[PDB]
Length: 402
Image 1 (cartoon, rainbow, N blue to C red):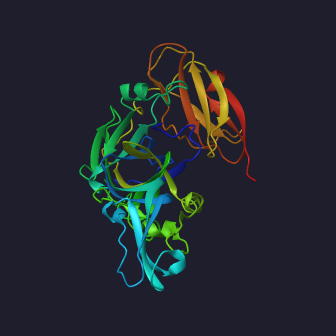
Image 2 (spheres, helix red, strand yellow; image 1 turned 30 degrees about the vertical axis):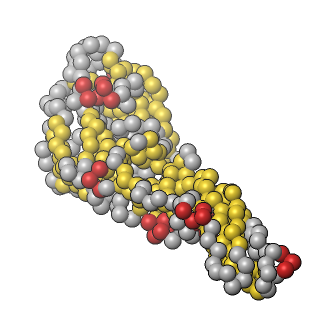
């Protein structure tokens, strides 16, 4: 998806009268149509963002498993108990004391030392990763509103074969690019990619099948056990475990409940990203300058088409205050310019609309060729009028207000 027709989110920019630069902000779910006097109309849209080489930072356990409990006890005054599970890193251990006497195995009375261990296993974890900024790629599409049909308007191969479209990537290393556009000229797009998706504010956090963009702030004060690529064991395991009251030589150890639910109140509540060895997202923005001084019109030279047109597709509402039609030209004198205006009444044929497809034309000498035309009609009732004199055709159009 590289141009605007059919997109549900669309914005219209009026380039200044005679300006050589145009500032843009490309919304990742949107499309810009830029119009300016004496210039062909352009669509530009941010297609997606891409980051490839993600480093790992830290993982959090939100559901722990407590298994294989064991206690070593000692009689009062005989020293500190040492449980040998302390030589095993997957065990968490805590010292303690219990009441001891003749009734539970000791010859003296008083506090006897105990050492209780339990195995800590992680059952499900949220793993966070980092994007280095040198590895973000913005995919951007550009389209110039030349001759198109209903079928090929969104076909990328057709439009790039007619030199009317380009997909290109901008990176922090290559923030500018010039593309040629056939006899329409060229445009240069100068972007700001490191200040588009600020990779220093965020982590990518994979939870099960999905991943998210999370504030590093929130990711750091997660009161959960954690690991990192180089660490030997889970750390701070104890905030998912309860050492229960010790009695003689026994002590119970349980895990707390899963925090899986409590992790989904956050991330509600966060930007989803597609993750498959490389992270893809369409949400986001890119700030660009578009240079248009070497962009010029093609057409103007040509004569007007002489023969009758017909409506190959009746006008349809595009959803953004414009209507799109497809014409069929019965004539053979192409290449010729299409006579198409928007009039408010058929007796007062003063033009009142405005063409989005500026300078629409039939490119070929073949008869019954099809041309698509996008127009911005005035509010209320109007007519789309194609052709002159007895070759003329019209279609009523209504554009509602509210």
